[PDB]
Amino acid sequence: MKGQETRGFQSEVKQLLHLMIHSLYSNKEIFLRELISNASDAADKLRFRALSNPDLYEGDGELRVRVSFDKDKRTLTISDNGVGMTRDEVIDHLGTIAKSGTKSFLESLGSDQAKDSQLIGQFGVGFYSAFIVADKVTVRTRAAGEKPENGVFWESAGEGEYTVADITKEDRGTEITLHLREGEDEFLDDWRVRSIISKYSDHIALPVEIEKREEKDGETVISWEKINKAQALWTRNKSEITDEEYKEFYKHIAHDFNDPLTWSHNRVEGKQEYTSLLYIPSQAPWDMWNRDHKHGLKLYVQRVFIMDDAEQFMPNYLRFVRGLIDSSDLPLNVSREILQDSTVTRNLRNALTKRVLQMLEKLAKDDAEKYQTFWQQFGLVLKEGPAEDFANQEAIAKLLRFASTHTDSSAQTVSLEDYVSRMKEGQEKIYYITADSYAAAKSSPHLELLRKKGIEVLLLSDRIDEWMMNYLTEFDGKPFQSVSKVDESLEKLADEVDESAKEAEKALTPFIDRVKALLGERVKDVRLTHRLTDTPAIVSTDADEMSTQMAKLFAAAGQKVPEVKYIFELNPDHVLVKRAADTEDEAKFSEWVELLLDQALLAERGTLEDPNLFIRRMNQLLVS
Amino acid sequence: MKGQETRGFQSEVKQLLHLMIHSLYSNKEIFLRELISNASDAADKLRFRALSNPDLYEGDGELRVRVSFDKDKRTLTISDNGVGMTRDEVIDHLGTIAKSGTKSFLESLGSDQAKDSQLIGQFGVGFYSAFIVADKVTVRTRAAGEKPENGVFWESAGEGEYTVADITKEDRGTEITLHLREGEDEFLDDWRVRSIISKYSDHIALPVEIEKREEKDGETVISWEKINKAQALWTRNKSEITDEEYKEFYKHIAHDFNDPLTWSHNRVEGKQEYTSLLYIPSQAPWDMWNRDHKHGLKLYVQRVFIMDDAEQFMPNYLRFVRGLIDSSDLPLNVSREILQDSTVTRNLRNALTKRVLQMLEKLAKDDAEKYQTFWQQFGLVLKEGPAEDFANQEAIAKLLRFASTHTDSSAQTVSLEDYVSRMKEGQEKIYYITADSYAAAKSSPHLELLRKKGIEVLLLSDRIDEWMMNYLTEFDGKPFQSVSKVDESLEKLADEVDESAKEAEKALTPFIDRVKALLGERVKDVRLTHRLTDTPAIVSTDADEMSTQMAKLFAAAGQKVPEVKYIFELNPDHVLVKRAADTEDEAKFSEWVELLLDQALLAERGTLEDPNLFIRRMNQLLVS
Amino acid sequence: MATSTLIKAIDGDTVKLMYKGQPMTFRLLLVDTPETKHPKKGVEKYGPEASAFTKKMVENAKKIEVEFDKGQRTDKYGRGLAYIYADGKMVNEALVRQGLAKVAYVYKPNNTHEQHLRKSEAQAKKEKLNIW
């Protein structure tokens, strides 16, 4: 018996506070998971640096991570023979996880400790999670190959401080003795540690061995038996790999801990032989629009590590992809400038571009809810897609999700695919209403006309959607119906006008004469017609913005065109013109009339002859 | 300069088109003016070259122009003994009047060919006028010091093309042979031509002789009779010069054909020998706001031309004053550098500026008509006057004319001295108001408070006035005052703003937080400033259009720049912002804030990004 | 969700096709097959509106660039001298010292006091006696 009565948890902004949501993980053992994940990236750094100096092995070639456990003192001791950590990698990173001032980018200049967000994404997760179940975490590390006396002692019990002291350890790699709290004996029980280790260690290439100690009379046999499959997730059989081992390997190679929506483990041989394993994050990275990486693929050449977070294997449009790539054909002496310049990496990243296409298209058809999560985190990124490659824009348009009139929500749940299913009989034209603001899309009157006839509309309300609009003129052999104008097609059909009848027009005739002679030659003509809408005044146009774009049109007078002075039309019935008609007094008659004028001009230009004429009359009727 | 590639037909009225229309002049014989004009300045350029080397006279000590006429062949040959015209001085001059591609200053850089319009102002009038009476114009020059073998040929029938070649002309100077049109035999009559010689040449320094030959049976007698006095207008008796000679000589030295408003012919004799002759133009020259010169006087030293467009004798304050100054005191070998730095030439410029003071202050009382025409064309530049010299500030303020609420005309006629009489009992302060545009500022009805109080306010819609006024703090004891705004925004120190201080700011801090998160990145920054005023909010700027015209101010993003996103500062005290803070409702909260945003934005841009949204707001709130 | 028809249509005024960007990024995505360029347009219908109320506003003037008339003139004479050259001797900012602008305003005072007292003396006279 428990009884889950009531709930409620709403928290956003700042990475650290979002880490604390899945810090608990409903497991606690997420600490041991992430701890060995750093020992995997330590083994990575070692095998890379071993290409520049094999002295790092110190003779001992056994690269492994060993977990020993004690009941008496209550200490869980995880010790890898990786690169370890230098005095730098401890003080300049673990110190910046404690009190220093990394903030989000940096306390002072906002640049120096900019590259600690990547480092907190990995090591920062294991830090707090360790202290969830550990009373004390003692890190006694030593850099492999480098002098034993430059070994680093580190101590904290979870406070915003660190006790750092230089010690000697002839053993290379990192040795972390976590004094677990009394009660956390589970992580010190053999069977439990077996299940815990295996769950993540199977994604890890580095053999994770355990203290199989037999404590018998005289026979106190200490043996180290590997609980992991001891095989790198990209090179082992996809049949042996379960879906979680992918999700868990992501957290290592991405320097993260979130659950990826989907992945793509494909091997491609030929001239360019590589094994690719890409993923799709459930989060938008902090550094998405920053000049540093949080996207990228960990470069391996022939199962050996070179560099992490290498975005050089992925186009900037596909920056949403996170994973790794093991090229067996690529040079082992390769560098980031080789990756930027050399043609082999250009053809390699284009060979990875298609792995992205399959992974997205699948996720789209498979689970559009996960693809909706992807789209609301990485939409702006994929919006560059149809705007670059207009050739395959139809194929990318299946991936494109827009906000529509299907709901009054800002959620881009409706697709061009969804719309194909929503299409009416005879409908060859997909109706679009475009705006750089969501509230400006909601300022559209054309919506009421679509509402009456029962045909569906896209509410384009994003910044970079206008860039794709330069190319996205057709999808699936079906053109778009742009709301670009209202036209004189309804010329003599203007009878369906509520009750704006000739009774009103008899009272309009003196009003017409007064307005035309009040405005004079700054307007072409003031015609009183029956446009309903919430707009009290609207204009009629001849050609391109009346005449603001052509040859003959500017050949009329040159200066702005005389014809361009728009045809000032009003709604006699609408309360603004009606309250303007109630006011016969010249001062306030001209206040209303010239207001409605520059309002209509503002609608068909965006710019005014006199902005201050308008802004006086506009703000004055709002205030007085 | 190496132009080419410039295809863009858009030129009308600007100089050349306005020249051709009034180069007809209903007169025809206006050609004969410009021919002798070019002959006088040519002989005067030989006088300048003679200072640089006497050998360039080619043996001729007597420099004059000799008109001759062939009645039968219908060709009129005006040949001067001037400098002539060098080969490049024919090609890059007459050729640029016919076919080249000068645009205005240069099609390429807009600088190199800027001295084309200087030549078109005189010789372009002479070109058109010539082809009115002439079917064909054939130019044969030979430059001073250049051997007869380097004689130059130019030929055109009035087309958009020319024929330039090298010929032999043993005579130095210029030979203009106009083949008159069939019927135009009027200008082949000796008595006719001599009457037209005297009519123009009388105000010209260069002796104009005519071919008096007696070609009888066997008797080929040849003589030359000078019809002109052969003395300079400026050096001849002031009372012997008629008004018409001043007016037409203005047109000569101004490179124009309009009438001057007024003039002043003076001579100064004794210690410092200089004759001064200044004219006031009726129309603003094209160079008024351009980087090449037509402002200033013509420098002569002892009836010898040195340089045209010499603004060394006349400041930017009087740049519009066009005429000339001859000095028998200053050196013949005087340099453009000596003209700026020398004390003798400073005394020249000082006496000339004071002589224009005597002309302008007279002209105010002499003809308020011509003085009002003067100020509305030239007073924009004259307005630098006080705000460059504090010593004469009061005496320049006597020349300063502004606009005031005397009349709703944009004609700036009213002086400060006028305002001093026009002051009321206890009206010690000169009420002024600066503006961007007269029509814009006139649309403001707030000034009706000053109407009923019976105060008059200075209307300022100039560009440079806002700077000039910074020193124009007081005139005649009366201190100037801005009625732009004053209130409790400072009252004692800061916070004396009704009571909008810390207590308000407790509610304003989560308000700023909400607004900046609502707009996201649409705006740079949003503040609550306690400028009480009668306006709800105001946007602030760094530089021009915030940042939409400078290097760093475009090098930020590259689109419309994050800097260009205006700083939105509201008054929390204002009743509309009280109602905006009273609104907890999401859609209406944002609507109020964004109303004041696009309100202030439209006041500083004259343009909205998405107009329909802001219009829909005023429509809804006013229809209700 | 979908409101009966489909469309949650809302307020209306005017419409414009959004645009500001066209040159951006580099070139690298899928393959060669260039053909998605074929637009369309059309409009032929108008509907009614339901917006009719009258609220109250809070009267107050408005600031900006200001110029206008009155109807008034008169003149003087005296002073007159000129010599300068546009350089940078008196190129600087200041303007205004102090002024009036006391046109009109509505002042609202408030203050109250009641308060009272009572106090009086009495007239005590002396007795008189006379004899023969």
Image: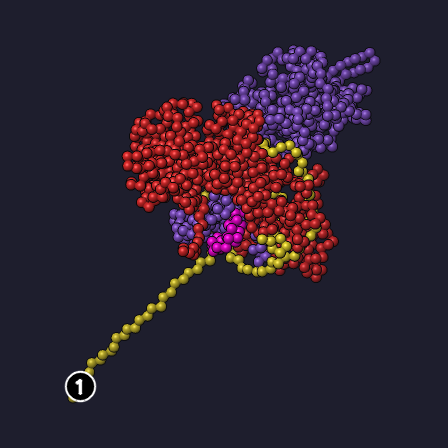
Chain colours: A red, B purple, C yellow
Report which quarter residue B147 is drawn in.
top right
Percent across and percent down for residue A375 are 55, 43
Disc 1 designates what residue? C130
In front here: B516 or B546? B516
The chain carrying label 1 is C
Quarter placement of the C terminus of chain A: bottom right
Tell me: residue A83, above or below residue A611. Answer: above
For the stretch drawn in magenta, what is the main secondary structure?
Answer: helix
Tell me: residue B388, above or below residue B172. Answer: below
Say if the magenta span includes residue B181.
no
Percent across and percent down for residue A212 are 36, 36
Q: Secondary structure at mark 1?
A: loop
Q: Write the residue at 79% across / 13% down.
A: B220
Q: Which residues are magenta?
A: B576-598
Q: Write the residue at 66% across / 22% down.
A: B93
In front here: B190 or B469? B469
Q: Write the residue at 62% across / 25% down.
A: B113
Tell me: residue B30, above or below residue B469. Answer: above
How dense is the environment of label 1, judged by Cα within 10 Å: few (below 14), some, or many (20 and up)?
A: few
Judge from the rendering whether residue B37 lies leftward or rightward of residue B73; answer left or right: left
Residue lying furthest bottom: C132
Q: Amino acid at mark 1?
A: Asn
Percent across and percent down for residue B575 are 48, 55
Q: Write the residue at 68% across / 15% down.
A: B142
Report which quarter residue A152 is drawn in.
top left
Percent across and percent down for residue C97 are 43, 44
